[PDB]
Amino acid sequence: AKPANKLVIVTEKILLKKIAKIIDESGAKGYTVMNTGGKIEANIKFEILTETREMAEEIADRVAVKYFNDYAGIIYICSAEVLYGHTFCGPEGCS
Amino acid sequence: AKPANKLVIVTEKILLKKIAKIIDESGAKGYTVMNTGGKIEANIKFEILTETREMAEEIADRVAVKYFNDYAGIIYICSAEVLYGHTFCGPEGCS
Amino acid sequence: AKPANKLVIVTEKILLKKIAKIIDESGAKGYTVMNTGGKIEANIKFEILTETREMAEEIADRVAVKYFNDYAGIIYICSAEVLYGHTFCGPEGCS
């Protein structure tokens, strides 16, 4: 039972590569992405689990500052506990 | 860090327009929708962030009463904090 | 307002049937599944609401032990309250 912060980013489809690049540079182990609708126009949704709150805010602050003046989008955070995940918890395990 | 209520509605694909219409009339700023499976048959999932609990229940109570006697579906709620989002937090920001 | 445990499983696409079969045998009422990306390669995401914590861990422990030595994936849990859902709450309702 390793606690975690689930960061969610919903925004326009064009930024996929731009946001994916930012997530990799933050220190996050991995992420999930999926095609969605919004209002209905096609857009994307990122889901990133992070060990610390600070890392989650670091990802949100950069994406918002860089693109949210021009492009539409929303970013929010949820509490979670990771039970299994080699990259997130390590070979040691989530215990 | 503006607190929010994440309302989730999973139900049959036919109701997309019917449920989308209800969400707009509730006072919710926007929503996300996506194609999913369930048991596997194709169905839809709505995700709505709301400022108050009452608004979330207002959306759930109407959709359930109107369609859940006939159609299959589930509605649940999650705690969240919106970090960035112009429509949800306003030009003032989520602070 | 019936409390629930939202179990989420993200893993490789091949295991869809293998994991779907396990979820059915656990005692979970139903589930949601959807095509997603991850890092970008195509993969799947399961979402299972469960009445007890023990049932959620039972599903996670079996899937992890059986496939997570070979295949990549992450499993985490979120708090939630089910407002409407005939299969989850019964004909009595979520109250």
Image (tube, coloured by chain):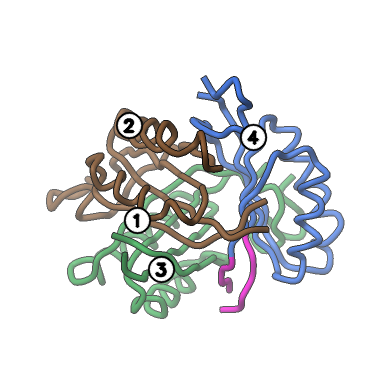
Chain colours: A blue, B green, C brown
Please tell me how many numbered marks the rendered image carries.
4
The answer for how far apart the CA atoms under marks 2 and 4 are is 22 Å
Residue C58 shows which numbered tag?
A: 2
The answer for how far apart the CA atoms under marks 2 and 1 are is 24 Å
Subunit of mark 3? Answer: B
- Do the residues indicated by labels 2 and 1 lie within the same chain of the protein? no
Q: Nearer the viewer, mark 3 or mark 1?
A: 3
The answer for how far apart the CA atoms under marks 1 and 4 are is 32 Å
Circles 2 and 4, Cβ within 8 Å, touching? The answer is: no
Circle 2 residues within 10 Å: few <14, some 14–19, many ≥20: some
Subunit of mark 4? Answer: A
The answer for how far apart the CA atoms under marks 3 and 2 are is 27 Å
The residue at 83%/64% (across/down) is A69
**Residue A77 image-quadrant placement:** top right
**Residue B67 image-quadrant placement:** bottom left
Look at mark 3 in the image and give the residue it sits on.
B44
User: Hey, which residue is sitting farthest front in the picture?
Assistant: C70
Subunit of mark 2? Answer: C
Which corner quadrant holds the N terminus of chain C?
top left
Q: What SS does tag 3 mark?
A: strand
Give, as a three-letter code, the residue at label 4: Thr
Circles 3 and 2, Cβ within 8 Å, touching? The answer is: no
Q: Nearer the viewer, mark 3 or mark 2?
A: 2
Look at mark 4 in the image and give the residue it sits on.
A87
Dominant secondary-structure state across the stretch colored magenta: strand
- Do the residues indicated by labels 3 and 2 lie within the same chain of the protein? no
Give, as a three-letter code, the residue at label 1: Ile
The answer for how far apart the CA atoms under marks 3 and 1 are is 12 Å
Look at mark 1 in the image and give the residue it sits on.
B75
Q: Nearer the viewer, mark 1 or mark 4?
A: 4
Circles 4 and 3, Cβ within 8 Å, touching? The answer is: no
Q: Residue A43 magenta-drawn?
A: yes
